[PDB]
Image (tube, rainbow over all chains, first blue to last red; front, top):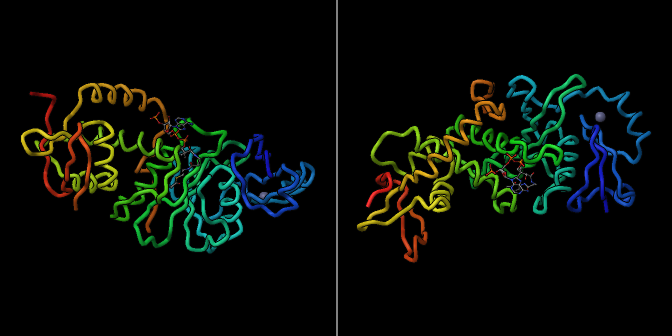
Length: 272
Length: 27
Ligand SMILES: CC(=O)SCCNC(=O)CCNC(=O)[C@H](O)C(C)(C)COP(=O)(O)OP(=O)(O)OC[C@H]1O[C@@H](n2cnc3c(N)ncnc32)[C@H](O)[C@@H]1OP(=O)(O)O
Ligand SMILES: [Zn+2]
């Protein structure tokens, strides 16, 4: 019954049960190494570990870097221990996360922010190496201390950048958590309105939008419906560009320039 | 390559491949 964790300089309340070994669980308090994600039972043991631990960032390859923001690609097979610890840590904040131990079939995309002591964990998403259903995200998490600052949408944007470069369309693995659904709705909205703002033509197929954005046709239609931009006039379906939504976006996109909370495709260095 | 949706009380079936017209809020 873990209530709290000490993670670097933060003290975080947990949301859900995670299956940590019982003799850790019963303390109700875990001390975590912020770099290798090893869990320990006291401050003093943590302090001892930090003196020995060489890790200043996630394992795997740094495939994105824009200044202090990185994304590391970590192979569940090559770095089993790290990926399990990450999954156990994630399940403290995920209601729905199934698995924690069998991480070999998964890639983990771990987003970090650098300061003078190292590259600190912001969040991550996991991805099946080979998904039967072409899911481009399995679970996604922003660490609580970083929530609602724009990092989540950057992680989501990053998941779709990978899909674009793979020349696939993608979708998050069902089921979507409540906060998952909200974040994805905000992102889908943003990219759909951006597309329609830039697009000059007289008509588009859902297919064409999906091809550009890597977003799944169903998710596009779902968003069009959400914004009440699908209509039916004289026996055919029309995309209705709402002026309120247009004006709202250019306003929201005027503050997106000075935000710095943006994934920049030119800062990716990756091949599947 | 279809989808089902309810728009203002009606129920509709929409193709993914068919181009749909873009309107700029007219009658
Ligand atoms: C397939 C799956 O993995 S589904 C599981 C998803 N993961 C989880 O539920 C685990 C816990 N949740 C999280 O870690 C986070 O909520 C995430 C990853 C879903 C989103 O991360 P964040 O860093 O908070 O996202 P970001 O800062 O980019 O904000 C995302 C959008 O969601 C909204 N949002 C985020 N949290 C909340 C909240 N508690 N209440 C209302 N809105 C919220 C933001 O307002 C924004 O939308 P807007 O621009 O339309 O207002
Ligand atoms: Zn360590």
